[PDB]
Amino acid sequence: GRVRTKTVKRASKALIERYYPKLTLDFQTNKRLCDEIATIQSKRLRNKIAGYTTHLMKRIQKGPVRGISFKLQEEERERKDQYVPEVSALDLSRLNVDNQTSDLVKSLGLKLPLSVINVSA
Amino acid sequence: MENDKGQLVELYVPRKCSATNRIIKADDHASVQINVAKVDEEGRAIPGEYVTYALSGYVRSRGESDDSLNRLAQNDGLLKNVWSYSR
Amino acid sequence: GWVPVTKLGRLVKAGKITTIEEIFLHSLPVKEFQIIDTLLPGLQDEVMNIKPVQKQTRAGQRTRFKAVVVVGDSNGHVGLGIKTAKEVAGAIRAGIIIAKLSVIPIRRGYWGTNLGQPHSLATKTTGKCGSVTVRLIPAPRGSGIVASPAVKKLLQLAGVEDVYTQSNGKTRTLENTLKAAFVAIGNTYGFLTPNLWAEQPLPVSPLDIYSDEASA
Amino acid sequence: VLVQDLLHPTAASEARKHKLKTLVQGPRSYFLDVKCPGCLNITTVFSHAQTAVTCESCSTILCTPTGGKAKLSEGTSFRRK
Amino acid sequence: PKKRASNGRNKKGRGHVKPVRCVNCSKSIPKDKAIKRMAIRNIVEAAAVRDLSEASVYPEYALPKTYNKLHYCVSCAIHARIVRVRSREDRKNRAPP
Amino acid sequence: SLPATFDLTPEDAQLLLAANTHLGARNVQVHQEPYVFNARPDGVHVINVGKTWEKLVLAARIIAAIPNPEDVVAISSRTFGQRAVLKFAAHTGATPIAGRFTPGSFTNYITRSFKEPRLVIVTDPRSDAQAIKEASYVNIPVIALTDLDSPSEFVDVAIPCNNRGKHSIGLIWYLLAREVLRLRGALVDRTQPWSIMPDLYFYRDP
Amino acid sequence: MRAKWRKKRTRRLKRKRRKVRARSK
Amino acid sequence: GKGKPRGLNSARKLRVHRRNNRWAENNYKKRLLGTAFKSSPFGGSSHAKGIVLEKLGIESKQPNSAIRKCVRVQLIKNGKKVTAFVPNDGCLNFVD
Amino acid sequence: TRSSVLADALNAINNAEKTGKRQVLIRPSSKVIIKFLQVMQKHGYIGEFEYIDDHRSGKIVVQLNGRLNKCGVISPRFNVKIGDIEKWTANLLPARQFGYVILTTSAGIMDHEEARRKHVSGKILGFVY
RNA sequence: AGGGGAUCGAAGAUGAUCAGAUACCGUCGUAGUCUUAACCAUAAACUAUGCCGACUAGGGAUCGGGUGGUGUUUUUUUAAUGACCCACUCGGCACCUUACGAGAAAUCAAAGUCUUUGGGUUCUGGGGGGAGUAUGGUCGCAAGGCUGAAACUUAAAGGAAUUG
Ligand SMILES: [Mg+2]
Ligand SMILES: [Mg+2]
Ligand SMILES: [Mg+2]
Ligand SMILES: [Mg+2]
Ligand SMILES: [Mg+2]
Ligand SMILES: [Mg+2]
Ligand SMILES: [Mg+2]
Ligand SMILES: [Mg+2]
Ligand SMILES: [Mg+2]
Ligand SMILES: [Mg+2]
Ligand SMILES: [Mg+2]
Ligand SMILES: [Mg+2]
């Protein structure tokens, strides 16, 4: 089988963790660059790391990959995290409170705009 | 305790649970100690000042920790009609 | 060097905690044995027995040794530790770390007319592990520790001079017999007594007063 | 609950509980004033008849026995006494 | 030791259950302890329906079904790729597959 | 006591009711929850939001009483509270735990994810039992957001809310952050509305 | 052997010992 | 009630129950039945004397392979034949 | 059937105190239950308690402080001689400094400490600590 | 002991299997199976858990009765009933979660409130074999039931879980 071990996989993931604005989707460029950024005691392992790095780059090009967080996607994912609407979904668009909830409103000694709609079994 | 002439003995007089008046043993890891802050006329918490509540691990294990603190906190002036004696 | 990693361990080096009863008062868990060594340097350790346990395997039995060690100074503190290892020396050494981590205080009392220096237990206490039940009854002056040699020297290391004992079940199980006695002595502080009926101001935990000496 | 006023249960709780299991047991039945058509002749019936109670003068029907509460006649006015 | 709480069966307050015979080996087994399975199948096949349609007057007739309630004993069920054996914690589950 | 400015303002009851925080569970009820108010038809039990607010303030006082902000821990495994806890830790020290809990984060002092909090805040006690279970081993108080059918074992002061809906979960996290900031004094004005939008603590599915 | 058939074996033995003893009285 | 009666007038039931139940005790049964007096060839005495009748080479049980060198003795006071051991290395030569 | 109403009174108190309950209801409130309870409250073991007068036998609602460890009845009520109180005090009391063996005597119901002062004994009812 | 006697079927007869097969498989097939009058008095007759009483954690379902709800549908749109829905309740068959507690453990809402040892009461056990055997009684037509040893022999039998 062609299942790749943790040494091939962890090293490939670590390179992507910090070298995204770097080596592209091409294996030939990948293997010519991985040996320059990281030292590997053998050529066979260095080819497997570059081959898996190429494979993992393609999966990044189509959506994110679970467990992979490089510089560019973490800043983009956090950039949309402050997105807020303008409709203010909690603000009133007209509130509808049932009969039992209406009893709660006056019990607390508070006056709110209510539109009571009855609900029955 | 103490001997015939003062001279307190029986080191380490232990704490007692607020909700059950039960000793919190040195090996009771479920027991907790709640510190709730105080406010002075501004809504700003005073550092270093707390109302302290100690609950044994027995009540916490039985699910009655939350209810017991409602009774404990209401009768100390820092809570309100959430708790009622008549159930 | 120790370089502990624990909020409680940091307070010991900073010196903010000087008595182990301050740990006992707030029920603070102890996860580093150097805390006990720093707070209680006067405790002594001893091994009751070593017994071999064997695991049946495809090729022969796998023999390992069970070490039962009792620690504690002769004034008010004992800890009991049990550990298995493939070597006897390693089990004994590892059985002392466990023993120190489980140090508990014993509540000593008088059989009556409290002249001074509590010589016995305050109340009747009992502890059951497995089938073994160990009962401890306060005894008058000079009666010694009326117990089996295994149970006796555990009570000798607890700072109790006079006590009566009754045992039940398969007491020849040495491990369970000492675990049943360790429960009984630990229960001396769980028994509420009329002289402890007074109210206390519920002192603040030391982890709050000395928060500056925490990890951050 | 570990604390509660066992001396003053709410009337809602005492309403739900069995009659023997209240703080002080009491019957949940009552007596009615039956308006038999025709003559006034006010008759008192129990909540649970166990018998076909009839008026003294015109003894046709006032109530029918049942496993629980008695069932009054089709045409009849009543008020709890 | 007691393997099961119900111990084999569904008898709690019955005393006696008036057994039924196994459909595979004629073994007597109490009806509650039996392993009843219901067999509801079409009259012919999933393959003969293609040929029994055009060769039939009354087009699209009914495709009727057969109904049969089968009882198995403890031995006959295990041997027939049925309730065979489970683990100690899986034994407690009573939900059908 | 209180300066009587902490009562439920008319705008606070707007947000609570518009987010349906008052809609509790069905007829399935726990005897440890007297917060039920006037059970609605169709089986829904309406939660007394007046009790929710006062309990919420009590929780906030405890959080502000802790000497170090980083000693608070917010844990949410539910997908509806994963965003809420993170931004709760954005405006407060409150070291967050979003996602898995890694059994042994409170014991096992040699683990990588070891934490020593003086208080734990959880969203759902049922789904966060692993966090609650270990807190019972190291003498750690726990603050939870308990619905009307949520378990209450080893749970200190709890905020009765509607954990079923995404609007109710995020709002309570939004509210709790606002009061703890006010108690600490970061929000100088009690009557100030904290213009930071309440939908900040609101999950998005895409 | 099975306890059932030890019960059966002994009963047959008691039959004969009840019969050989009848030859005398 | 945990079995046994507790009533303050139940002394007879407890006393009779204990008396009946003691017959399950081997020592109580042996002592009262007088098994020592009617069996156990001694007359309930510590020692007894007799006459050697034969020299025996009783073979030991398992696991053990030896010859025990016992003797056969007929008791003077009773007349019962019993087997006795001659314990030591080479003491069977003195009991011919 | 109900043999002794004091055992059910004391067992309910024990089961209430084990759970940490501040109160417990006792039925059907005999006299010796009150006398036994009054001794417990005199030494501060229970606190306040309330008698509910229904017309059949009465009920008692006892307020329970957390100080009580065990209350129990001794059945049967053995006759206790004056010199045998030290035996009963020894067997079923935790220590010589606290605990009371409550016994009924011709001079009312009282603990063994009061019985020693009055130098009178009788039948044993129970114990409290 | 009469009736009945289809079916299945101790025994028996047969075919087969087998080294043997007086067994399992096959075919027959008597007693029996069914019933009436009278015996027998046993069972893993089991929940392997005596009965009465009190208290102690949560949850849903179900069976019987009762209560309440302008609740839904059928009559006579319409009332009462009937059947459903919601809430409560008394009693029953059980079930799910947990372990305050118990247990050697398996497990247990009782097998809990038992060295902090006492609510009332009945019955039974005291290492394994010999042995539920002998003998004597008593009951049965018989088979057998109930009661029930001793001589002798032995250092272990046994329970629950663990790893192979
Ligand atoms: Mg013994
Ligand atoms: Mg088996
Ligand atoms: Mg009497
Ligand atoms: Mg041998
Ligand atoms: Mg029998
Ligand atoms: Mg039967
Ligand atoms: Mg029911
Ligand atoms: Mg019903
Ligand atoms: Mg039933
Ligand atoms: Mg014996
Ligand atoms: Mg025996
Ligand atoms: Mg076995």
Image (cartoon, rainbow, N blue to C red):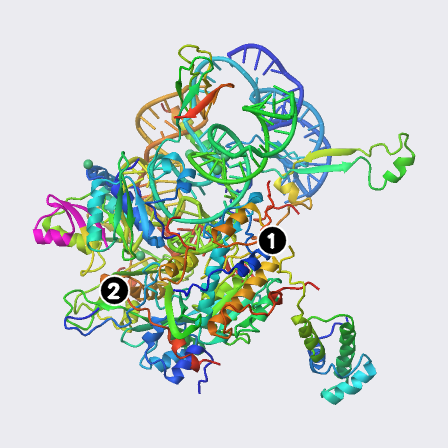
**What secondary structure is found at the residue carrying circle 2?**
loop
Q: Which residue is mark 1?
A: A95
- How crowded pointer 2 is (Cα within 10 Å; few <14, some 14-19, many 20+) is rated as few
Is I53 positioned to the left or the right of F117 in the image?
Answer: left
Which quadrant of the picture is home to ligand 5? top left
Chain of the residue that carries numbered disc 2 in the rendered image: C
Query: Is disc 1 on the same chain as disc 2?
Result: no
Instruction: Locate residue J25: give its quadrant.
Output: top right
* Residue J134 vertical position relative to residue F147 in the rendered view, above or below: above
Near-viewer residue (D30 or J152):
D30
Count of residue discs = 2
Q: Which mark is residue G16?
A: none
Q: Which mark is residue C198?
A: 2
Q: Is residue F79 magenta?
A: no
Is I58 positioned to the left or the right of E19 in the image?
Answer: left
Residue F130 on image: x %, y %? 53, 63
Magenta-highlighted residues: I102-129
Distance from label 2 to label 1 (Cα)?
Answer: 55 Å
Task: Residue H47: tell me if it is visible.
Answer: no
**What secondary structure is found at the residue carrying circle 1?**
loop
Residue F15 on image: x %, y %? 57, 59
Tag 2: residue type?
A: Ala
* Residue E79 vertical position relative to residue F191 in the rendered view, above or below: above
